[PDB]
Image (spheres, rainbow, N blue to C red):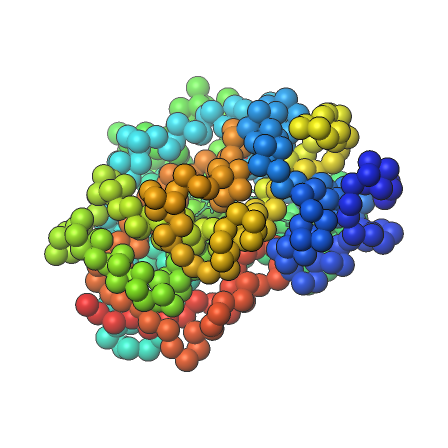
Length: 457
Ligand SMILES: CC(C)c1nc(CN(C)C(=O)N[C@@H](C(=O)N[C@@H](CC[C@H](Cc2ccccc2)NC(=O)OCc2cccnc2)Cc2ccccc2)C(C)C)cs1
Ligand code: HEM
């Protein structure tokens, strides 16, 4: 079992029994990957408990697994712990289950729908500005994540469901309260450490109704969507929620609820985390913040409201987003379960091996980015933009299994950026941690919440 990579002549760190190389994650897995690539070259192997994982860095080899051989050999991700009814969520579904969900849902995020989401989010822009404006009157430091989370919460419920929930006016509110508790994939937590290591356990927890998602959070989330469904049943916009009732003429009751959670989570978690990273970056590189404010002000003269089209006009904003995602790619790795023995670009890979693309590492590889640790948007300009491999920069993954809400995360993040910047400026203070330190566990977050001060323009 543990001799796989030795017998295939692939480098790697030497693994202990039972544990695999799991202990090397103590320094966080993004750093572990760094060390590895650096130590072992272009390809290397390790063991997550008894699980072989092959890291891969060749840009072609990557396009092969992500784009060409996806449907036939690398279709799935790693199965991960007790999930229960959430076993049908799109991000977790496999093979045949997945293809349908992927096409049943993909039509949620087309131009027409995206354009149609603008004016609803336009309402939640103001409430954000107006909210932050009060902190600019109180004049004491701000938890970006808090207030961006609220914004995030507001926009996902209202678009994917058509049901306003007024989160921003609620410093206290059950929706966010529960959605943040939904999954902390933390190794300090013996639980995740132990399932991840000893997976022979997972089927047992599945019979005992235990789940990685607290029974609590999921109870409140099932009931909410249970209800949001029957709200619509009362009235007489084809959206996420709609599209799925329309399928109820093959997507079942619980199936319908499970997509919502994924969406809700994605919508809430990702969006707010990234926006906090960017505002940190802007406020620690003031030149860029002014540059961005000028661009915005030039495209949206005298605080004029952002629209679908103006947003895509904003080239620097895009450079700013892209560079922050380079530095902080919130999925730190991409992964695909190899389901049949196969040979990709001069390499055999046996059935069952998890193939793994260390995004965080590839993003910081001093072999593809001059001064890779530094925040430099100009690397994303038209001028320098073509010199950038689409299989090295993978913040939304790639191929058929790539991020389904990319275009919606982006439009939405920018919408919020614009509206903030065209009213406020942001500055470091005494509790603002410099430079930033990622936390060690599953999620890519800062170990201390993002706090900045806000001046009113
Ligand atoms: C110790 C070793 C095995 C580990 N490696 C990792 C890193 N890793 C593979 C992860 O991505 N972590 C976890 C994870 O969040 N990914 C899985 C888990 C499904 C999880 C569903 C979920 C999550 C939280 C709460 C409720 C439901 N993912 C999910 O739906 O993601 C929403 C999302 C996130 C980012 C961008 N777009 C969408 C799927 C996924 C991963 C990356 C991007 C998109 C989907 C699981 C593997 C447990 C964690 S533990
Ligand atoms: C900036 C915010 C976001 C980042 C950085 C991001 C990143 C990703 C990445 C890298 C993947 C994996 C691609 C792959 O595995 O090849 C992913 C998967 C996915 N994302 Fe996004 N995402 C973001 C926002 C969203 C939003 C807003 C939604 C939905 C509303 C979303 C829904 C999904 C789903 C459902 C999957 C699994 C796709 C599948 O297996 O078919 N994520 N996310």
